[PDB]
Length: 122
Ligand SMILES: *C=C1C(=O)CC(c2cccs2)CC1=O
Image (cartoon, rainbow, N blue to C red; front, top):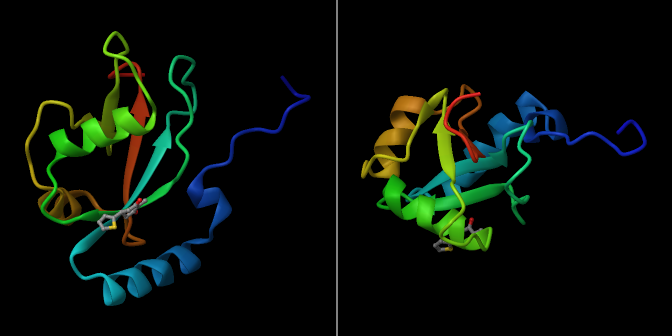
């Protein structure tokens, strides 16, 4: 509805220059944390909004563990599907530690971006 404001993403809220410097600050103060931005897919109609956007994830945590953490934050029940996507592909099947996902998939600004949805392609 045009009466209600559109959802604005992290990259629309913070400029690239600010994001680049945020990550430099984060990396300096927390070298063992991965800076992750987790957002709901723009067209999502079945899953609620997350109470935070930026997560400093310990670098040993794997993707299966992170998925459980987000499902819990969203208070999902077991009959609700949830997919976590990085750069256009699903992280749902894997046990890769997030440290490795960061090196493979991080944005130019230094953040690792993830999108969640109730479907795997859209
Ligand atoms: C939103 C967060 C938290 O609630 C705590 C997380 C921590 C993980 C290990 C030590 S603190 C960081 C975070 O982004």
